């Protein structure tokens, strides 16, 4: 989850 968000932003 943390990674998904980091990449999205």
Image (cartoon, helix red, strand yellow):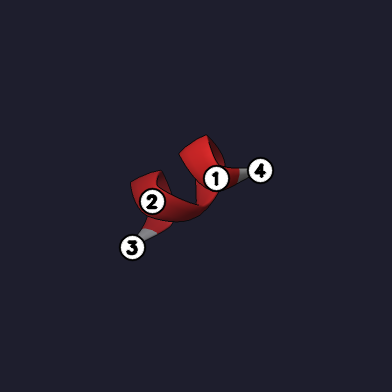
In the picture of the structure, the residue carrying the numbered disc 4 is 9
Q: Is residue 3 above or below residue 7?
A: below
Q: Is residue 4 left or right of residue 7?
A: left
Q: How busy is the neighbourhood of tag 2: few (under 14 within 10 Å), some, or many (20 plus)? A: few
Q: Is residue 1 above or below residue 9?
A: below
Query: Pointers 1 and 2 in contact (CB under 8 A)?
Result: yes
Label 3 – label 2 distance at C-alpha: 5 Å
Q: Secondary structure at mark 3?
A: loop
Q: How busy is the neighbourhood of tag 4: few (under 14 within 10 Å), some, or many (20 plus)? A: few
Disc nearer the start of the sequence (4/3) = 3
Residue 9: percent from the left, percent from the top? Answer: 66, 43
Label 3 – label 1 distance at C-alpha: 11 Å
In the picture of the structure, the residue carrying the numbered disc 3 is 1
Query: Pointers 2 and 4 in contact (CB under 8 A)?
Result: no
Please name which of the two marks, 3 or 1, marks the residue nearer to the observer.
1
Query: Pointers 3 and 2 in contact (CB under 8 A)?
Result: yes
Residue 1: percent from the left, percent from the top? Answer: 33, 62
Q: Looking at the image, which residue is at 37% across and 45% down? A: 3
Identify the residue at the far front of this view: 8
Label 1 – label 2 distance at C-alpha: 6 Å
Please name which of the two marks, 4 or 3, marks the residue nearer to the observer.
4
Q: Is residue 5 left or right of residue 4?
A: right
Residue 4 numbered tag: 2
Q: Secondary structure at mark 4?
A: loop
In the picture of the structure, the residue carrying the numbered disc 1 is 8
Q: Secondary structure at mark 2?
A: helix
Q: How busy is the neighbourhood of tag 3: few (under 14 within 10 Å), some, or many (20 plus)? A: few
Residue 8's image quarter?
Answer: top right
Label 4 – label 1 distance at C-alpha: 4 Å
Query: Pointers 4 and 1 in contact (CB under 8 A)?
Result: yes
Disc nearer the start of the sequence (3/1) = 3
Query: Pointers 4 and 3 in contact (CB under 8 A)?
Result: no
């Amino acid at each position: 989850l943390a990674m998904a968000l980091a990449q999205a932003l």
